[PDB]
Image 1 (cartoon, one colour):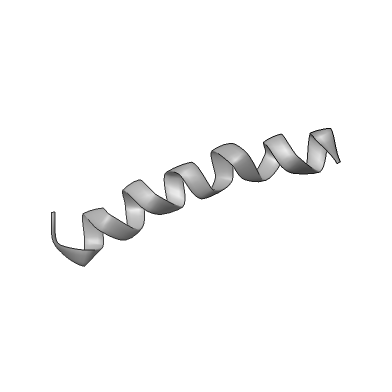
Image 2: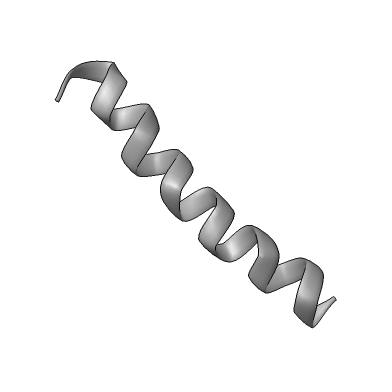
Length: 25
């Protein structure tokens, strides 16, 4: 955990939807 696993699990979704937008946009 810690802010480390928090920035890895959060950044993981950031990209997941990131490409989802550029594609639908």
